[PDB]
Image (cartoon, coloured by chain):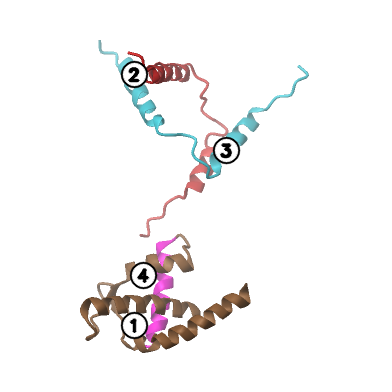
Chain colours: A brown, B red, C cyan
């Protein structure tokens, strides 16, 4: 769904960034959850309760791991991005979905 | 981090009512002394002449 | 005296809304130096030791 794809986009961004930093090898693509909170905060907003937003974020992440894209948080609240994302997020899908998103903006406007 | 705090909105709302039945007064001789020293200083600072 | 006036209730209510909106604040930098000097003087006077 939409918001899930939003998170997907954020993840893929981090994925590609680290892939550059480390080469396109195995999945040492690790992120710390706290870093997502700022980024996602801009779009879904801020219900003014850090715990509430963490509940939201983890609910999303969970749902993603249902699609197999992400490991759930470890002891250090870090997760690794499943590489399957990149194929879910190849430029072709990005462009198609982006066109559809522009279409939706047009319909709403 | 689970430590709840008060938004400024609540700060204001409280400051409206706890100083409502007894709004501790400001029209006070000490307040006048305060203003007087305030001017004593502000003038002397704004007076460029040696 | 045939001339209307503002009950104190109005004074408090008005000084409330003004502080409320997010225009720039009631107090400002000098306030700090103000509490500073007044505290100095208040202590010095309050001190009974000659």
Residue linked to disc 1: A70
| Chain for numbered disc 3 | C
Q: Mark 3 packing: few (<14 Cα in 10 Å), some, or many (20+)?
A: few
Pointer 4: what residue? A36
- The answer to whether the residues at label 4 and label 3 have Cβ atoms under 8 Å apart is no
Looking at the rendered structure, the secondary structure element under dot 4 is: helix
Tell me if label 2 and label 3 are in contact, CB under 8 Å: no
Mark 2 and mark 1: span between their CA atoms? 65 Å
Whether residue C23 is visible, yes or no, is yes
Q: Secondary structure at mark 1?
A: loop
Residue bounds of the magenta highlight = A49-69
Tell which residue pokes out farthest to the right in this image.
C2
Q: Residue at left 45%, top 19%?
A: B35
Tell me which residue sits at (29%, 13%) in the image. Answer: C48
Q: CA gap, disc 4 to disc 1?
A: 14 Å
Give the CA separation, mark 2 to mark 3.
Answer: 31 Å
Residue C18 - label: 3
Q: Secondary structure at mark 2?
A: helix
By secondary structure, the bulk of the magenta-drawn segment is best described as: helix
Q: Which mark is residue C41?
A: 2
Is there any visible trace of residue A67 in the rendered image? no
Tell me which label, 2 or 3, sits earlier in the chain.
Answer: 3
Upstream in sequence: badge 4 or badge 1: 4
Residue lying at 62% horizontally and 72% vertically, measured from the top left: A109
The Cα–Cα distance between marks 4 and 2, rounded to whole angstroms, is 52 Å
Establish whether labels 4 and 3 are both on one chain.
Answer: no
Q: Position of residue C32 (x, y in %)?
A: 37, 31
């Amino acid at each position: 769904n939409l918001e899930q794809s939003l998170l997907v986009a954020i993840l893929r961004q981090h994925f590609v960034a680290w892939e550059q930093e480390s080469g396109t090898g195995a999945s040492q693509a690790q992120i710390a959850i706290d870093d997502l909170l700022p980024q996602l905060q801009i779009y879904l907003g801020d219900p003014g309760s850090e715990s509430k937003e963490r509940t939201r974020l983890l609910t999303l992440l969970d749902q993603l791991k249902g699609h197999g894209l992400v490991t759930s948080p470890d002891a250090h609240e870090r997760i690794v991005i499943r590489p399957i994302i990149a194929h879910l997020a190849d430029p072709i899908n990005l462009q198609a979905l982006l066109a559809w998103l522009r279409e939706q903006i047009a319909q709403q406007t | 981090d689970g430590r709840i705090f008060a938004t400024d909105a609540l700060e204001v709302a409280i400051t409206f009512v706890e100083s409502l039945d007894n709004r501790f007064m400001t029209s006070t001789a000490s307040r006048l002394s305060t203003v007087q020293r305030e001017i004593e200083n502000l003038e002397t600072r704004l007076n460029p002449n040696p």
